[PDB]
Amino acid sequence: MVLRKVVAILLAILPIFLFAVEPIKVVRSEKEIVVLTRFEEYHFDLEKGILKDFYTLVDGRKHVFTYGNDGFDVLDEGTPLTVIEEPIVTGVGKVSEGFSDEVSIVYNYGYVKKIFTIKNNENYTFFVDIENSKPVDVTVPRVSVDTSTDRYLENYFASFNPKTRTLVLLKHDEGLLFEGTLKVNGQKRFIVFMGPNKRTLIKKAFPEDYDVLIKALVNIPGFNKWYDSVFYGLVWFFWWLKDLTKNFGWAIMLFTLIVRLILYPLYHAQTKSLINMRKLQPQIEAIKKKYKDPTKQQEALLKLYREAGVNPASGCLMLLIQLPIFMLLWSVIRYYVEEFAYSGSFLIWKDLSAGGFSNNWLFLVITIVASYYTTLLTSQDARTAWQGIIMSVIFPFLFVGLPSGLFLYYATNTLIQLAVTYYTY
Amino acid sequence: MVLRKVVAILLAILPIFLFAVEPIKVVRSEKEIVVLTRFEEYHFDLEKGILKDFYTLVDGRKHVFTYGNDGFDVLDEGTPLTVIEEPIVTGVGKVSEGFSDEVSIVYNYGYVKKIFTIKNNENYTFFVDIENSKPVDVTVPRVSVDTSTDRYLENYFASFNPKTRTLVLLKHDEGLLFEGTLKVNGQKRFIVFMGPNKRTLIKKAFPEDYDVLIKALVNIPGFNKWYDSVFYGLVWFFWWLKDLTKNFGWAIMLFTLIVRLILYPLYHAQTKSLINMRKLQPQIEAIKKKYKDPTKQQEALLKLYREAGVNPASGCLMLLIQLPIFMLLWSVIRYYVEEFAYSGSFLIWKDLSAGGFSNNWLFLVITIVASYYTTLLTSQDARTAWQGIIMSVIFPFLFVGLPSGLFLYYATNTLIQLAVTYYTY
C-alpha cells in the first residue's frame, strides 16, 4: 500500500495544493470592508455603500483611485442615499479567509440593490448589478486629473489617467445619451474596467466592439506612448503564438527558435571564426612554455595570429545583441503577468513571471549539464574544467532572481546550441 | 579580461557578499533606542538610561523581560538619577543602518558613565562598563516571577525564569557580599548573560568557574527538565565532534557514519532478506501474466513465497528507527542555531539550521542522482523508472522545508548506502 499511496494518494493531491490559485481574501472590518486579489484590491465603505479607494498590486502597491464623490454614489436628485441594513458578502467557493471563485457584495437601501460582483479572473473588470423600484441616479468613477481625457463614447465611457496609466472604462446601455451620472430604472448589469491600459485585457473585457473602441482610445493624448507601436506589435505576436501553442512556455520556445533561426548565420560565423581558431589553438600553435611569460609583453601571439581571416571576441559579442532580445522578452513577461498567474502552468513552473531559486533550480541544473557537454567539444585544452564553472555555475546563480520565463528562453536556446553544435564530423 | 574578471573580480568578491553576516541594525528613535541582532533584541530608554524591554528572536519573538524598576537603574539611596545629555552610540565597523562588529551605548549623568557594550557574537552576553566619581548603586535585572529561583552565588548572581526558560546570570566582583543592587565606586566592567539556559553558551560565557557555576544551576528547581540528561549528553557529544572536525557539517557526517556503523547489521539483514528476495523476484518466480489479476484474491503469492526465511517489509521498517535518530539530530540542530549562524559556513551551505529550496537544492539533486544509481541494482524489473520517482523526487520535495543539516545527514547516509551497496559480485 506504500506504492498505491504514492501513485494515487500522494500523486493525485500534490498538484491540487501545488497549483492552488490564490483566493480572494476578503477582510470585513469596522466601517470598512476590503476585497483583495492577486493584483486587484478594493476598499469599500459599508455605510454609504461605495468604493472608497482602489489600489494596484502589480509591481508594487499603487493607489490609483480615491473617492471623489463619484464612486457609485446612489443619489436621488443631488443628495445621496444611505443603507438600511448591513452589507452581505455573497461569493462562490467559500474558502477560510474568503471566497476563491467569485465575490459579490450586497448593498440595499430602500428599493434598490447595488450588487458588486467581482470575478476571480485575470481582468481588472467587475460587475455593478442593480435593481430599483423607482428611478435613481448613480455616480460614475473617474481617475483623470482633469476632464480632457474622459471620452463619452457610444455605449462606453473612458476615464484615462496618463500619470498612473490607469484607465476607467465601463460599458453602459445608454447609446451616446449620457448625462454625467447613470440614470436607471428597473434592473441593469454594468461592466466596468478599472486598471492599466493593457490592450490585450481590454480585448477580452469588451470583445464585441473592441475595434471600434480602440480607435477612440488611441487618440486620447498620453494613452499611446511612442514605443507602444513596436511594443504592441510584439505583444500581439506573442498573443498569436500563445493562441497557437496552448500556452506561453511553448511560445517562448518557438520564439527562441524563431529568434535563433531568423538570425542563424552567426553560428557559422561564431564557429567559422572558431573552426579556424579551435583548429589552431595553443596546442597546434604548440607555444605554451615558451620564450616568455607575464609582465605583459605579449608582442607575438596577437599579431602573429592576426593573419588568419578569423573573428576574435566571438563569445563576448553575442551578449550585445542578446540584451535587446532579453529586454524585449523580459518587458513582454512583465506585460503578461496577470495571464501567467491564472493561465494554468507549463509543466512544473506554475508561473513563469516569478523568480527565485524555487522555480529556476531545474533550469539551473539543466543549464549546467547542457553547458558541460557543449563546453566539452570547444577548448580541447584543460580550460573546460574552469570553463564549465564560469558560464554555468556563476552567471545564472548571479542572475537567478530573474523571471523564470527568461531562464526558459535561455535554456531552450542552450538546448538548441547543444543540438546545433552537435554535428560531429 | 573576461576570464580575469571572473576568476578574481567575480570570484574574490562573491563569497564576501554571500557569507556576509547579519549586522547589528541599530534604530535610534524618539524616547527609545533599539538594538537588534540576529537573535538578541533590546529596547533602551534614553531618559532614565535603562533597558526597557528585552525580546528573543529564536523560534519566534519572545518578550522575556519587562522593566521592573530593576534594569540597571543608577540610583543614589533609593531615588534614581537621570541623564544630563543625549546618549551616544559608539560602535565598530559602521555599516549603513548600524554597526556590524560591536555596539556601545553611552549614558552619562553627572560623574558616572554607564556604557552598554554589545558584541556581535553568538552569545546572549553584553557588558555593562561603568565609571564614577562618587559611590553609587545600580539595580540588577531579574526575570524570575517569584524570588525562589534567584541564587546569590559567590561572584555570580542567577535569576532563572522556568516559565520562559530565560536565565539572567551576571558576574560581579563582590564575592558573596551582595546586597540587592550593585554598589560601586571607581570603574568596573560587568559581564551579563541574559537568554535561554543553553549550557554550551554558558560555558563560553563563564569558562573560568563554569564547573563550580553549573553545580549550583542544576539544583535550581525547574532548570533541569527530565530529558536534559540524555539530551545534553548528546549535545556535548556533538560539541566534542565539532571540536574535533573543524565544524558541524563534518560532525554530522561522522555522526551519520557512527550511527550507520554502530548499528550496521541491518544492511546485511535488509539485503539478506533482499538477497533471497532480489534473487527470486517475479522474474525468477516467473509468474507475471498468470492465473488471475485484481479483484484482490491474492491467495497464492504471499503464502507461496512465505516459505523462504526472508524479512518482508524491509524498506518500510527502517523509517521507524529513523524517526528517533532524525528527531534527536533535528532537536540538536535547533539547539546550536546561534553557533550555526556565526560559525562560518560548511562549503556552500552558509547555515545548516535553515531550510527552503535555496540551500537544499544541491542536496536534492545529489540525492536524485545517487538514488538513481542505488535504485539501479535493486529491482531488476521495470519498477526502477517508477521507483526512482517515488523516493528521490517526491518525499524530499515534500520535506524540503527542513533544516539543511537534516538533509546533510540524509545525503551523507545515502552516499554511504551507495558505496555500501556497491559490492558487485
Image (cartoon, coloured by chain):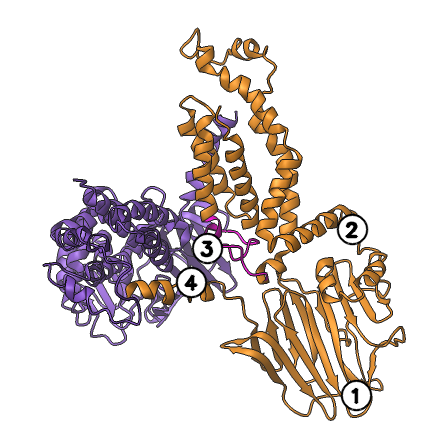
Chain colours: A orange, B purple
Image-based side of B81 in relation to B319, left or right: right
3D distance between C-alphas at marks 2 and 1: 42 Å
Q: Tell which subunit mark 4 falls on.
A: B
- Three-letter amino acid code at disc 3? Val
Which secondary structure lies at badge 4? strand
Residue A186 is labelled as 1
Which mark, residue B26? 3
Q: Which residue is mark 4?
A: B44
4 and 2 marks on the same chain: no
Q: Which mark is residue B94?
A: none
Whole-angstrom CA distance, mark 1 to mark 3, is 63 Å
Question: Which of pointers 2 and 1 indicates the residue nearer the eye?
Answer: 1
- Distance, label 3 to label 2, CA atoms, is 45 Å
Whether labels 3 and 2 share one chain: no
Magenta-span inclusion, residue B205: no
The residue indicated by pointer 2 is A225
Q: Nearer the viewer, residue B66 or B254?
A: B254
How far apart marks 1 and 4 lie (CA) works out to 65 Å
Q: Amino acid at mark 4?
A: Phe
- Main SS of the magenta segment? loop
Residues in magenta, as a range: A343-361
Q: Residues within 10 Å of mark 2 (few under 14, many from 20)?
A: few
At horizontal 66% and vertical 44% (from top left) the residue drawn is A328
User: Most extreme residue toward the top, as rendered?
Assistant: A291
